[PDB]
Amino acid sequence: PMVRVATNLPDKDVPANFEERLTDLLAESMNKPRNRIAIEVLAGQRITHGASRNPVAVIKVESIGALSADDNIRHTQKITQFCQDTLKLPKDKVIITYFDLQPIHVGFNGTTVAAA
Amino acid sequence: PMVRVATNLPDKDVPANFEERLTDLLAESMNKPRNRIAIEVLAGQRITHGASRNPVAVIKVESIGALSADDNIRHTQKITQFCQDTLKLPKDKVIITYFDLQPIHVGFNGTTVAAA
Amino acid sequence: PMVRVATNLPDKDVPANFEERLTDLLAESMNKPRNRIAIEVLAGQRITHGASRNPVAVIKVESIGALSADDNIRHTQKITQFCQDTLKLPKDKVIITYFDLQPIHVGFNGTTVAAA
Ligand SMILES: NS(=O)(=O)c1cc(C(=O)O)c(NCc2ccco2)cc1Cl
Ligand SMILES: NS(=O)(=O)c1cc(C(=O)O)c(NCc2ccco2)cc1Cl
Ligand SMILES: NS(=O)(=O)c1cc(C(=O)O)c(NCc2ccco2)cc1Cl
Ligand SMILES: [Zn+2]
Ligand SMILES: [Zn+2]
Ligand SMILES: [Zn+2]
Ligand SMILES: [Zn+2]
Ligand SMILES: [Zn+2]
Ligand SMILES: [Zn+2]
């Protein structure tokens, strides 16, 4: 899984253990090994929602599978509660997009996943 | 809609009202509510186009629908004109990718849009 | 092609010719014109892989075709080698996602590529 979390909260408000904790959360919920999860964090960024600059996170989650309709309900509930607990965001200021990828469209260790 | 606008123009050159005006523009062009529109702006960034560092914008627009072939002609005309007016970019310096999402792949308010 | 290279390596460590040389690399690999290749470089960013902050690059490659299964093996080999050479990254610290776009989802010069 490859996750990007962007927020307009400052970098000092996104704790240093955020990526590690999010890596544990997605490992368990997506059944993926920790060494196949990458997390990008972009804090202090300009972001609006409804043109408001109130605190918000916009997250992208890519994975090869593990993204059925029902799995995404569960990942959304978990990531949303996690951002509430760690970033203090309201439950309605966490916007997530999922991308279910084929292994032909992922490169790792110098070739595609499909070709590994 | 979840929109990301990246530019090599300095942050001081993307006016504070950019997100507001672009929110209004996309609400009208996509027939989407203002409170379902998020805009990320990333200025001051390293970007090249044909390896040139001349001013350019690279924009991603995600939406659940409202992205037909015909719709996308209208969004591109409107966004490209808006970047020309506000950022002074040439008409051939605004690069846009559209992602038409299913509602099972968007998380908002703690569950998927499909499950809401 | 529209390529995003994010890395936790500092900006001073990503050479000023990085984008020139990647633009040549992608033009030859994908058989796409140099003036249809944009690259975004986001260095100095928070990234973990397996929760490690060791040096890593997370890259997204979007293209109107040229991303067959076999094509993606070649692009992964070349881009991974290229990051080993220029950024001093290990082979297993280069994570790539490919997105194969329809021309109705790409806006350039004020209209879609499909409608050019
Ligand atoms: N190991 S796997 O086939 O389940 C696998 C699964 C995935 C996946 O994203 O599901 C993947 N994504 C790219 C990546 C992220 C971090 C390191 O490589 C790579 C691999 Cl090898
Ligand atoms: N209201 S809606 O069902 O048309 C809707 C539609 C969309 C959409 O993107 O089309 C959407 N994207 C996620 C989001 C962006 C900003 C706040 O939530 C969310 C919702 Cl709830
Ligand atoms: N020339 S083309 O039809 O093969 C073409 C191909 C692509 C493509 O991405 O394959 C494309 N992407 C948008 C873009 C990137 C840089 C400048 O415009 C645009 C065009 Cl016009
Ligand atoms: Zn920091
Ligand atoms: Zn599942
Ligand atoms: Zn600013
Ligand atoms: Zn307004
Ligand atoms: Zn620099
Ligand atoms: Zn060259």
Image: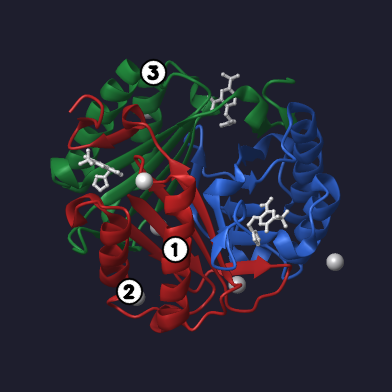
Chain colours: A red, B blue, C green
Q: Tell me the amino acid under the disc marked 2.
A: Phe
The C terminus of chain A: image quadrant: top left
Alpha-carbon span between mark 2 and mark 3:
36 Å
What residue is shown with label 2?
A18
- Tell me the crowding category of disc 1: few under 14, some 14 to 19, or many 20 or more residues within 10 angstroms, Cα based: some
- Tell me the crowding category of disc 3: few under 14, some 14 to 19, or many 20 or more residues within 10 angstroms, Cα based: few
Circles 1, 2 touching at the beta carbon (< 8 Å): yes
Alpha-carbon span between mark 1 and mark 3:
29 Å
Q: Does dot 3 land on a helix, a strand or a loop?
A: loop
Above or below, C97 against A90 in this view is above
Above or below, B57 against A54 in this view is above
**Can residue B58 be seen in this snapshot?**
no
Q: Tell me the amino acid under the disc marked 1.
A: Val
Residue closest to the eye, B65 or A54 = B65
Q: Residue at x 74, y 31 (%)?
A: B68
Q: Does dot 2 land on a helix, a strand or a loop?
A: helix
Instruction: Left or right? Give the position of B5 relative to C85.
Output: right
Circles 1, 3 touching at the beta carbon (< 8 Å): no
Question: Where is residue A32 shown, x and y percent of the image?
Answer: 24, 51
Q: Which mark, residue C68?
A: 3
Instruction: Left or right? Give the position of C101 relative to A54.
Output: left
Identify the subunit bearing mark 3.
C
Question: Where is residue C93 shown, x and y percent of the image?
Answer: 19, 47
Residue closest to the eye, B17 or B34 = B34
For the residue with label 2, is its CB less than 8 Å from the closest atom of ligand 4? no
Q: Residue at x 35, y 57 (%)?
A: C43
The answer as to whether the residues below labels 1 and 2 share one chain is yes
Identify the subunit bearing mark 2.
A
Identify the subunit bearing mark 1.
A
What residue is shown with label 1?
A5
Question: Where is residue A66 shown, x and y percent of the image?
Answer: 35, 45
